[PDB]
Length: 23
Length: 23
Length: 54
Length: 54
Image (cartoon, rainbow over all chains, first blue to last red; front, top):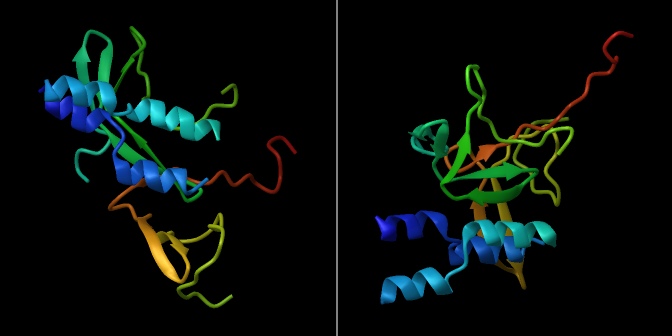
């Protein structure tokens, strides 16, 4: 349960990279 | 120990969204 | 695709919305699982967007 | 005014979004699906020509 909560609730590297280079 | 290390080190998706909002 | 932004009761008036990504003018915003309260003795609407005040 | 597949630098308020492509040095760095299979699109706000009560 803690691992699933971590996976759902934490920013993944691809998303953060794409948004960071999107602005 | 790996679980708590990953929870501490990795950034929250809410925090990343707020920071991306700031820029 | 089926469970994206699914709104389920967590406990009391607090409801849990699952994670999901929205597109705003081509910009992708990802939201984690979150909780929000309803309004007692009323039919409330849970949505995503921006208000005139905010 | 012909309808076809186009690539622009800005999403029109009236369009069918397919993808957002970030490319650099002649190579694509990232592709993001903008379809309903991946994201829930916040609809554009298009005001009417005549204000209410006019």
